[PDB]
Structure formats: structure tokens, C-alpha cells
Amino acid sequence: SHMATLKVIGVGGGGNNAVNRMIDHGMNNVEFIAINTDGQALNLSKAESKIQIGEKLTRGLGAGANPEIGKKAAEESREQIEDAIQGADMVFVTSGMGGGTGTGAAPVVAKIAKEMGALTVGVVTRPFSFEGRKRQTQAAAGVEAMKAAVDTLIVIPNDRLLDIVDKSTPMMEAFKEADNVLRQGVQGISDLIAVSGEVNLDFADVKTIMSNQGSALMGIGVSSGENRAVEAAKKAISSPLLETSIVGAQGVLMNITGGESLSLFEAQEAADIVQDAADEDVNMIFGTVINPELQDEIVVTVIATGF
Ligand SMILES: Nc1nc2c(ncn2[C@@H]2O[C@H](COP(=O)(O)CP(=O)(O)O)[C@@H](O)[C@H]2O)c(=O)[nH]1
Ligand SMILES: [K+]
């Protein structure tokens, strides 16, 4: 009764890319769905479920950077999108904003998922500044449309990738770092749903922290040794890639996983790190999992909303 069905939906080129790379990484008990106008992109997708939208509009090509085409394509394929989502308790929609299919279709996909009762999370990118103003303006319109259609939204400005690379870092490695935001969020929620805790949080706690909230932060931190709880908590909340930082969070789900050495003192330390960084009076849903396979490692999972 506890095993909520999670689906990750990539919409458009960048979304499809993220799905392919997450499948390559390995991720079980999550169903992947690839949605695109671009038939050739879908032919290369590794997702078990593929939905080609807008064939009568685009003749099987991509949207050619036109959000109107992405929106029309998704609206006309509503039933096929519904069929793929059916059964979902939680849907993550990922897309690169600024082109046509992601910008236009991802908000339609999210609205369909929300009206099917799924807890609906968007994780989307904004374009690099070097792509120019029209891409950014189109992306802004997509982001606003996404915000209206999801329960929670995580935006990754691609310009932040320029903050974490050196002059040689392969573009594909930078893209994998952006992928981690979505992948680790999904994994942390999957683990929370599946693993019974000593202070047990479940999918109903996820729904409470995320339903109808707007901006969100999802983070995981892992540390060991001295100060592990503080360091893990800091890692969970500190991503350089996020538009929405922890500052201003008024609601937090925090789950700590450790071995039998997990101390009460360090749990409070981790909670205090999150509360202080939010710089608000935070309402916390606190959970603890004891994994005796763990020795000195501690894992802190954070979901923050209420901005
Ligand atoms: N981090 C990241 N950003 C991407 C990727 N592909 C594309 N983008 C970005 O997503 C934007 C839209 O590209 P797209 O290929 O998704 C256009 P469409 O949705 O029409 O297919 C691009 O302008 C670019 O900013 C990607 O794999 N990783
Ligand atoms: K649980």
C-alpha cells in the first residue's frame, strides 16, 4: 500500500537527453517516458514508453524552436499522454526550456499529470546566455506556464554550469551534473517511499511538503567522519546549479539515514543547519532511517518548499 508509482517524463530534446542519461546510470522502480515531436530523437530513446506528438503538424520533425508547435502538438495528443501516465502517483516532468517542444509541450504534460491526481514536479533548465534573448524570453514563458501546471518546480539555469566547469570539462560531463539534480531527487524520494524508517516518513509526507507549493529545492548530501551530519546537511542544501536556493524555505522534509551510531545530537545539528540556512522559522517533517549496513556514513535528504 506504500509503494507509490513514480514516472519520469522527458519532453523535447533536452528532456529526452536527461531520460536517456538517467536510464544509462541505472534507475529501477521508476518508469521512464520520452515525449517528442522529433521522431528521430524518439527512435534513439532508451525509454520503455515513447510518445511521438504532433506528427500531423511537424511531419515527424522537431518543433524548430517554436513553442506554439509544442503546445499544439501536446494538446492534440492528450489521450496518448494520459495513457502513458495512467497509474502514476508521482510524475517528474523534465525539459529544456527555450525551444519549441519542451517550452510548449512540457506545461501541457504537467497539467495532464496534475489533473490525473499525480504529485507533479517539474525540473527544467533555462538556456545559456550565449543562446541569446529570444531563447531566454521563450524559456521564461515556458517557466511561468510550468509553474502554473505543477505542484513544485525546480529551475536549473544552464549558465550555472559555467560556474562548475574548468576550461576543459566536456560538455557531456557538465550536462551529467545538471542531470544529478533530478536523478538524486527521484532516488531520495524512491528510497523514502520504500525504506521503513525509525521515524518513518512516507509518500503522504512527500505530498504534504510538495503539493501546490511552487518553487522547490531537492537535495541529498553524504558525509563521513567528524562533523558528518553538518557536512551532509550542508551538501544537501548547497547546489550551485539552482535558481531556488534554500534561503526563504518555510517548509522542509529532512530525512537522515545512518548506521546504528546515528546520534540524537547530530540529528539536531543537521536540522539546525537547514533551519539557519533557510533564515526562516522552518516547519520540518523530520525522518530517520537506521541502515545497519552503514558504518560511518550519514545521508541527509532535503525537500524544501514554502518560498
Ligand atoms: N542542461 C541541458 N540543457 C539542454 C540539453 N539539451 C538542450 N538543452 C537546453 O535546452 C534548450 C532547448 O533545447 P531542446 O533540444 O530541448 C529544444 P526542443 O524542446 O524543441 O526539442 C536549449 O536551448 C538548451 O538551453 C541537455 O542535454 N542538458
Ligand atoms: K518509509
Image (cartoon, helix red, strand yellow):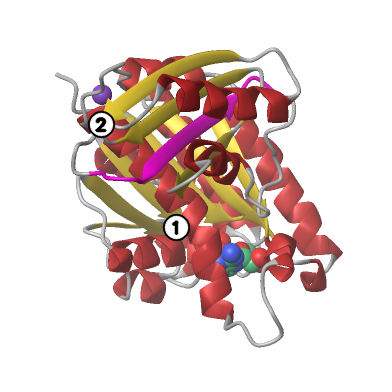
- Judge whether 148 appears above or below 218 on screen: above
Q: Is residue 306 left or right of residue 230?
A: right
At label 1, the amino acid type is: Gly
Q: Position of residue 106 (x, y in %)?
A: 52, 46
Is residue 2 left or right of 147 when viewed as pictured? left
**Residue of label 2:** 260
Give the residue drawn at x 46%, y 15%. 285
Which label is found at residue 78?
none
Q: Nearer the viewer, residue 187 or 138?
A: 187
Q: Which amino acid type is marked by label 2?
A: Glu
The magenta span reads 294-307
How far is mark 1 from mark 2, CA to CA?
54 Å
Q: Is 299 placed above or below 213 here?
A: below
Quadrant of the image occupied by residue 144: top right
Count of numbered circles in the view: 2
Does 180 appear in magenta? no
Q: Which residue is mark 1?
A: 54
